[PDB]
Image (cartoon, rainbow, N blue to C red):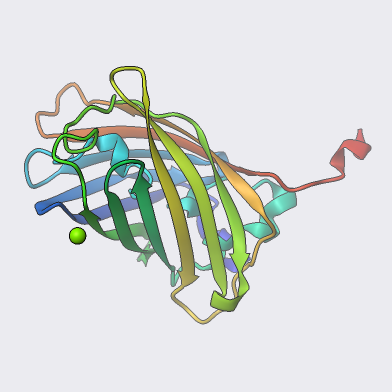
Length: 233
Ligand SMILES: [Mg+2]
């Protein structure tokens, strides 16, 4: 697709999130860049309202899959870039096992030459001292696959996946993700065969930053589609 042309180099990224979890209101602003050639994201997020009322790892998935590296042989399956520059709406339900849920709505689009992710997050039915509001989740992140399928009726896609958040006692907090993406513009998009995004995420801190924040290095690579290239060798 035509949109893929927008991603051949380093693209600046801005992320802005407004959240309410159990009446705890907060905002996050992120800045960095993406280079889809390497499936690579480098971002720093700051909670601009004070202390973040949920653990940072629980927000990683909400906080630009247009930066995934789609191998050449699978580029006809890249919905995300094909919707650019007009963008897409991304909605999720994130169900924390034995606890509350996030509902998110985002618009991901270009503003000039910057890729912007604007998000509203609503969390309900969290337990006062469960793993989320009780801050019992380690500051780390496990690799996962995002399983994508076409939704041709909506001219878009759906995804399903499980995030496993490590609890500080050695256990796991499951976060089931259900996702839908639909284009903002009316131009044609790519509707993919089933495949997945292999995602690896590393969380860190800026040693000179006093605000509540998260430094993220993430690699995202599309996979899962059959090719006959081995025959070439
Ligand atoms: Mg109720």
